[PDB]
Image (cartoon, rainbow, N blue to C red; front, side, top):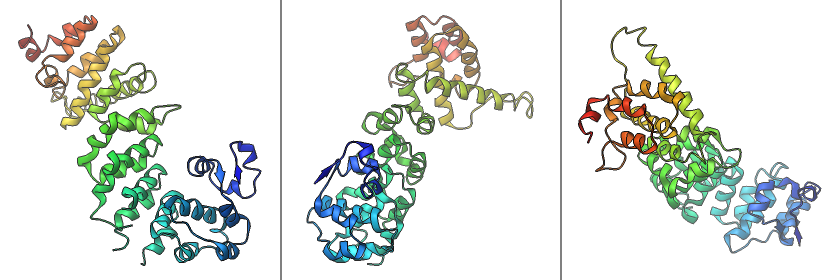
Length: 343
């Protein structure tokens, strides 16, 4: 048959080029069978005239995709119906729906309880949609299978979330956390923080990272990895948040003269802690001002003597001496709580 790795020798093929380059490498493995290329060069009615399906899932998938990218636009608006006929598994069409993002495909299988079953390949359709960022397909699955949404999310070690994150699909990420907030912290931690590690490679997907860092445990892990993150992500994020706080504080000591300097919820408070930990971890004179300012908040100051590791105590103070961050120490021992537990 034929095999292409040379991109220039791929866009020269009037037919093959119709297939997304990414797919041709991740699904077709740079090679195309003869019983499949046929379905792309001959007319549509001819391709089906011959179209003999396969027994193994991937067989059909690679085929159905060849017909789609070559005829779907050309009156083959009913290729999903004919497919079902000839011999394409009801689930294979559901995969090509989650991959191509074609709703029309799902619309057909949605007019035949045999849908709340086609869970196929451990919710592979749900996972394929997340990796391709097809939010609309993802939702249709949650619409055609309410009592299953939670298994799809946690399917394969929160795969959906992870695949979404490494591809930069922040919109697929948001929704996923809306579908079940009780799994947020989970998905983020899944597989030793898969999401963050892969959204950070290369040029990186800053939309995912910045979002991900709104999770105290996430920022906790990332901020300590100064080499991998920091100059690129953490630092700009901390500088961007320390300044945002100075603009709600001053904008309170304006509207509510001489009152409180607080963070409403527990979550924003924990963030300040690790945000402060990083500033100290960096050990720098120019960062002294942001440290004092963070400790001025009762939602952070009343979190200075604590520690991430249960059973331990003064972490920040320990970290300060550990690095030799004099000035951060003096600033810390100024807190009564931290003044008590002191040796």
